[PDB]
Image 1 (cartoon, rainbow, N blue to C red):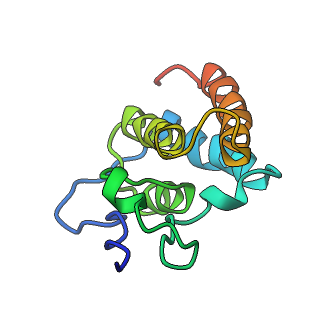
Image 2: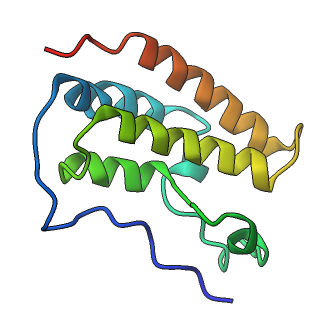
Length: 127
Protein backbone atom coordinates (compact mmCIF):
# COMPACT_ATOMS: atom_id res chain seq x y z
CA UNK A 1 0.00 0.00 0.00
CA UNK A 2 1.05 3.68 -0.57
CA UNK A 3 1.60 6.16 2.30
CA UNK A 4 -1.28 8.61 2.95
CA UNK A 5 -0.91 12.33 2.15
CA UNK A 6 1.08 14.09 4.93
CA UNK A 7 -0.89 16.12 7.51
CA UNK A 8 -1.75 19.62 6.39
CA UNK A 9 0.86 22.22 7.50
CA UNK A 10 -0.61 25.31 5.76
CA UNK A 11 -4.15 26.44 4.98
CA UNK A 12 -4.65 29.88 3.28
CA UNK A 13 -8.20 30.14 4.75
CA UNK A 14 -7.14 29.98 8.49
CA UNK A 15 -6.46 33.19 10.51
CA UNK A 16 -2.98 33.81 11.98
CA UNK A 17 -1.64 35.23 15.21
CA UNK A 18 1.48 35.38 17.35
CA UNK A 19 1.24 34.34 21.04
CA UNK A 20 4.10 34.05 23.53
CA UNK A 21 3.26 30.37 24.14
CA UNK A 22 3.38 29.67 20.34
CA UNK A 23 6.70 31.60 20.06
CA UNK A 24 8.12 29.50 23.04
CA UNK A 25 6.90 26.22 21.48
CA UNK A 26 8.96 26.85 18.29
CA UNK A 27 12.05 28.71 19.54
CA UNK A 28 12.46 26.68 22.87
CA UNK A 29 10.47 23.32 23.03
CA UNK A 30 10.80 22.12 19.44
CA UNK A 31 14.43 23.42 19.06
CA UNK A 32 15.42 21.37 22.18
CA UNK A 33 13.52 18.16 21.27
CA UNK A 34 14.86 18.31 17.67
CA UNK A 35 18.54 18.29 18.79
CA UNK A 36 17.88 15.27 21.12
CA UNK A 37 19.68 11.96 20.25
CA UNK A 38 16.32 10.05 19.90
CA UNK A 39 14.51 12.74 17.83
CA UNK A 40 15.45 11.45 14.33
CA UNK A 41 12.55 8.79 13.92
CA UNK A 42 10.01 11.57 14.74
CA UNK A 43 11.48 14.37 12.50
CA UNK A 44 9.23 13.44 9.51
CA UNK A 45 6.03 11.43 8.86
CA UNK A 46 6.21 7.65 9.28
CA UNK A 47 7.27 6.42 5.77
CA UNK A 48 5.56 3.00 6.04
CA UNK A 49 6.77 2.08 2.50
CA UNK A 50 10.49 2.90 3.16
CA UNK A 51 10.32 1.38 6.72
CA UNK A 52 8.33 -1.75 5.51
CA UNK A 53 5.42 -1.24 7.97
CA UNK A 54 2.39 -2.51 5.94
CA UNK A 55 -0.12 -2.39 8.88
CA UNK A 56 1.02 1.09 10.14
CA UNK A 57 -1.66 3.13 8.41
CA UNK A 58 -4.27 0.36 9.08
CA UNK A 59 -3.69 1.04 12.90
CA UNK A 60 -2.60 4.73 12.96
CA UNK A 61 -5.56 6.76 11.60
CA UNK A 62 -4.24 10.09 13.12
CA UNK A 63 -0.49 10.23 12.25
CA UNK A 64 1.68 13.08 13.52
CA UNK A 65 5.40 13.88 13.62
CA UNK A 66 7.77 16.76 14.72
CA UNK A 67 8.56 17.78 11.11
CA UNK A 68 4.86 18.51 10.57
CA UNK A 69 4.50 20.25 14.01
CA UNK A 70 7.49 22.48 13.22
CA UNK A 71 6.08 23.32 9.78
CA UNK A 72 2.72 24.13 11.46
CA UNK A 73 4.52 26.59 13.86
CA UNK A 74 6.64 28.28 11.13
CA UNK A 75 3.44 28.72 8.97
CA UNK A 76 1.42 30.13 11.96
CA UNK A 77 -1.01 27.22 11.30
CA UNK A 78 -1.81 26.91 15.06
CA UNK A 79 -4.04 29.49 16.75
CA UNK A 80 -3.73 28.02 20.26
CA UNK A 81 -0.71 26.40 21.95
CA UNK A 82 -3.06 23.55 23.12
CA UNK A 83 -3.26 22.38 19.43
CA UNK A 84 0.53 21.99 19.29
CA UNK A 85 0.55 20.08 22.64
CA UNK A 86 -2.29 17.79 21.40
CA UNK A 87 -0.18 16.96 18.29
CA UNK A 88 2.97 16.09 20.29
CA UNK A 89 0.65 13.89 22.52
CA UNK A 90 -0.79 12.24 19.40
CA UNK A 91 2.78 11.57 18.12
CA UNK A 92 3.77 9.83 21.36
CA UNK A 93 0.54 7.80 21.94
CA UNK A 94 0.65 6.71 18.25
CA UNK A 95 4.08 5.26 18.93
CA UNK A 96 2.83 3.37 22.09
CA UNK A 97 -0.26 2.16 20.17
CA UNK A 98 1.48 0.65 17.13
CA UNK A 99 4.53 -0.71 19.06
CA UNK A 100 4.79 -2.62 22.40
CA UNK A 101 6.12 -1.75 25.89
CA UNK A 102 9.87 -2.36 25.92
CA UNK A 103 10.49 -2.04 22.14
CA UNK A 104 13.49 0.23 21.34
CA UNK A 105 11.39 2.85 19.52
CA UNK A 106 8.99 3.04 22.57
CA UNK A 107 11.99 3.64 24.89
CA UNK A 108 13.10 6.43 22.45
CA UNK A 109 9.66 8.11 22.49
CA UNK A 110 9.37 7.85 26.35
CA UNK A 111 12.68 9.72 26.79
CA UNK A 112 11.63 12.38 24.24
CA UNK A 113 8.18 12.76 25.94
CA UNK A 114 9.94 13.19 29.35
CA UNK A 115 11.93 16.23 27.95
CA UNK A 116 8.78 17.53 26.27
CA UNK A 117 6.71 17.35 29.51
CA UNK A 118 9.51 19.16 31.38
CA UNK A 119 9.78 21.92 28.73
CA UNK A 120 5.92 22.36 28.81
CA UNK A 121 5.99 22.76 32.64
CA UNK A 122 8.32 25.82 31.98
CA UNK A 123 5.84 27.31 29.42
CA UNK A 124 5.35 31.07 30.17
CA UNK A 125 1.98 32.46 31.25
CA UNK A 126 -0.15 33.99 28.44
CA UNK A 127 0.65 37.75 28.05
